[PDB]
Image: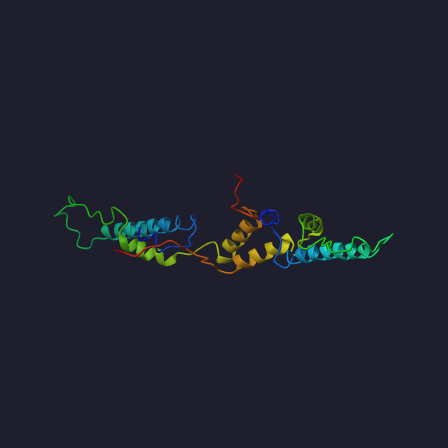
Length: 103
Length: 103
């Protein structure tokens, strides 16, 4: 809900990217963990991995807060202004309005 | 009031003409009467003009109904459409609308 009143003029095809961006960032943190989990120096067989790491089982908040910094509105202000000018080029009761019938 | 809901898209400078048109038509009927009032044939001095004619002491309805037939809208539909497009080129809350404050 905080993402709602922060992204005002974003199109629907744009905030479907920032969740794919935060997904991509969390996969980057997961493979980052799995490239150093097997990189154990003085790898003792004692104290086995019966407790798993499980570093990122879901998207955290700072993944969103980092992926949100690359947000970008696709449509400009000049094209939403173009479609509003097309809505008024369309009629939408282009005329009198608010009349009544004789008794 | 019947002239109101009959002249819809007339400008204010246009129905100030049709009352000058009905005035001009009633003056035409008044001088029409005064060009035949003094044109009495077999003009007897008996039965004097102690009762005046007074043919048109005000504008009648058919003066309006005849002058209304030469009504003409000055502004077109393309220029009222131009000013509405200028109203939307103007902002008039060109944006979000309808937000609230946190509790």
